[PDB]
Image: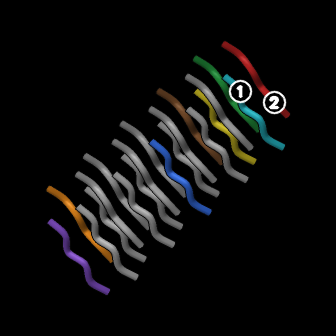
Chain colours: B cyan, C red, D green, E yellow, F brown, L blue, Q orange, S purple
Amino acid sequence: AADTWE
Amino acid sequence: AADTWE
Amino acid sequence: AADTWE
Amino acid sequence: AADTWE
Amino acid sequence: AADTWE
Amino acid sequence: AADTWE
Amino acid sequence: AADTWE
Amino acid sequence: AADTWE
Amino acid sequence: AADTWE
Amino acid sequence: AADTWE
Amino acid sequence: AADTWE
Amino acid sequence: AADTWE
Amino acid sequence: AADTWE
Amino acid sequence: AADTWE
Amino acid sequence: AADTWE
Amino acid sequence: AADTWE
Amino acid sequence: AADTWE
Amino acid sequence: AADTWE
Amino acid sequence: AADTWE
Amino acid sequence: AADTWE
């Protein structure tokens, strides 16, 4: 799983 | 943004 | 699954 | 499951 | 924001 | 599980 | 911020 | 930012 | 597990 | 796992 | 800051 | 910053 | 385990 | 494991 | 600062 | 700064 | 174990 | 293990 | 400062 | 500064 944001 | 999971 | 947005 | 918001 | 769980 | 926020 | 656990 | 886990 | 913040 | 941010 | 434990 | 663990 | 901060 | 920051 | 223990 | 342990 | 600080 | 800083 | 023990 | 131990 991966959770990305700025 | 992205949230990827299974 | 994937959930994407800005 | 995933719950996303700003 | 993101909350991911199973 | 993962819980992310600013 | 991120909290990751299983 | 990125949080990656399995 | 990991818990990160500023 | 990896958790990255600035 | 980071707290990592298992 | 990066926190990497398994 | 490791706990880091400034 | 590794935990890096400035 | 860092505190590392197992 | 870096803290590396296993 | 190690505990470091300034 | 190694813990480095300035 | 550093305190190292096992 | 560096503290290295095993």
Image marks 2 and 1: residues in contact by CB distance under 8 Å:
yes
Subunit that carries the residue with mark 1: B
Identified by mark 1, the residue type is Ala
Q: Which mark is residue C2?
A: 2
- The quarter of the picture where the C terminus of chain Q appears is bottom left
Q: Chain of mark 2?
A: C
Q: Residues within 10 Å of mark 1 (few under 14, many from 20)?
A: some
Name the spot of residue B4 as percent of width and height, x first: 77, 35
Q: L6 and D4: which one is in front?
A: L6
- Vertical order, L3 against Q3 (above or below): above
Report the side of Q5 relative to F5 (left or right): left
Residue at image x 44%, y 41%?
L1
Q: Residue furthest bottom?
A: S6
Q: Residue at label 1? A: B2
Q: How many marks?
A: 2
Mark 2, other Cα within 10 Å: few <14 / some 14–19 / many ≥20: few
Q: Secondary structure at mark 2?
A: strand
Please report the residue visible at 25 percent of the width from the left and 68 percent of the height from the top: Q3
**With respect to residue F5, does S6 lie above or below?**
below
Residue S5 image position (x, y, % from top left): 27, 83
The quadrant of the image that shows the N terminus of chain Q is bottom left
Question: Where L2 sits versus Q6, above or below?
Answer: above
**In-image side of S3 versus B5 (left or right):** left
E1 versus E3 height, above or below: above
Q: CA distance from mark 2 to mark 1?
A: 7 Å
Residue located at (71% from left, 26% from top) = B2
Residue F4 occupies quadrant:
top right
- Dot 1: what SS? strand
**Viewer-closest of L1 and D5:** L1
